[PDB]
Amino acid sequence: GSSGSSGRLLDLENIQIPDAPPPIPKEPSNYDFSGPSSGIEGRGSSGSSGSSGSSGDKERHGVAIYNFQGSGAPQLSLQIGDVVRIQETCGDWYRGYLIKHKMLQGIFPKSFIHIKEVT
């Protein structure tokens, strides 16, 4: 085998994060979702059935690095040090929910989500 030189040996590990987070990007174009017409959310209706078999149980593990403050869906709030279950990915925004608190679901900027790939 053949290997070159290295240069990633320190005593204070710390991700290469900037002093401050960049200006959140612009919302993605008219989403291309698909399902039952949404509107009776306030009224309330049971029925959260979907994937029956094994369509694709391969989600992405991310972590919030910057404190995001939203107002309401589809916008979702996030807190640094929080992990979310990434299901889909549109434009410059992710689609999922807070694993710790599923009670809240929506989208968020990818620039705020740290995709962990330790595997």
Image (tube, rainbow, N blue to C red):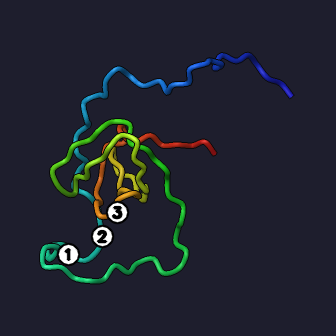
Extreme residue toward the bottom, this view = 46
Q: Amino acid at mark 1?
A: Ser
Image quarter for residue 43? bottom left
| Left or right of 16 in this view: 29 | left
Disc 3 crowd rating (10 Å Cα; few below 14, some 14-19, many 20+) is few
In front here: 90 or 102? Answer: 102
Q: Which residue is mark 2?
A: 34
Which residue is painted at 22% across and 57% down in the image?
A: 74
In whole angstroms, how far apart are the C-alphas of marks 3 and 2?
Answer: 21 Å
Residue 45 visible here? yes
Residue 82 position, x and y percent, is 39, 47
Image-quadrant location for residue 39: bottom left
Regarding mark 2 in the picture, which secondary structure is present there? Answer: loop
Query: Looking at the picture, how far across and down is residue 8, in whole percent?
Result: 63, 20
* Contact flag, marks 2 and 1 (Cβ < 8 Å): no
User: Which residue does the image show at 38% across and 22% down from the upper left?
Assistant: 18
Q: Residue at x 52, y 43 (%)?
A: 116
Task: Please name whichever residue, 90 or 46, is drawn nearer the observer in this view of the structure.
Answer: 46
Q: Residue at x 36, y 56 (%)?
A: 98
Q: Amino acid at mark 3?
A: Lys
Label 1 neighbourhood size at 10 Å, few (<14), some (14-19), many (20+)?
few
Q: Which residue is mark 3?
A: 102
- Is 63 rendered above or below residue 21? below
Q: Secondary structure at mark 3?
A: loop
Gap in Å between the C-alphas at discs 3 and 1?
A: 22 Å
Q: Amino acid at mark 2?
A: Ser
Q: Is residue 96 visible?
A: no
Which image quarter is the C terminus in? top right
Depth check, mark 3 against mark 2: the one in front is 3
**Which residue in the protein does label 1 denote?**
37
7 shown above or below 116: above
Say what secondary structure mark 1 lies in. Answer: loop
